[PDB]
Length: 109
Image (tube, rainbow, N blue to C red):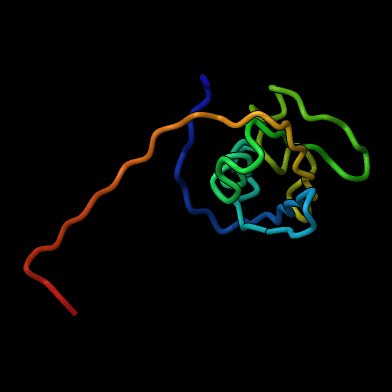
């Protein structure tokens, strides 16, 4: 992944609805600027290694996004206001490694 993530907080906001094959669905809040990928990152964490290398697609135009689509901002993909990205399961899981951290400056409340 050449294009990395850019943690930024802007006034603008975008609505991205995530539909699942099971039935449930989650909708996060991302900046109209945030790259489509952003949504893919969250969804991947929300479901984790449940579906695997799943994918994302539209609902109306039913057009399978492209590597480029993830390179352009959301608002650019006409997903500024309301967007509906359906999660398409693949079947094969995606091996990964987790981590853990902890710290406290003699402070407890």
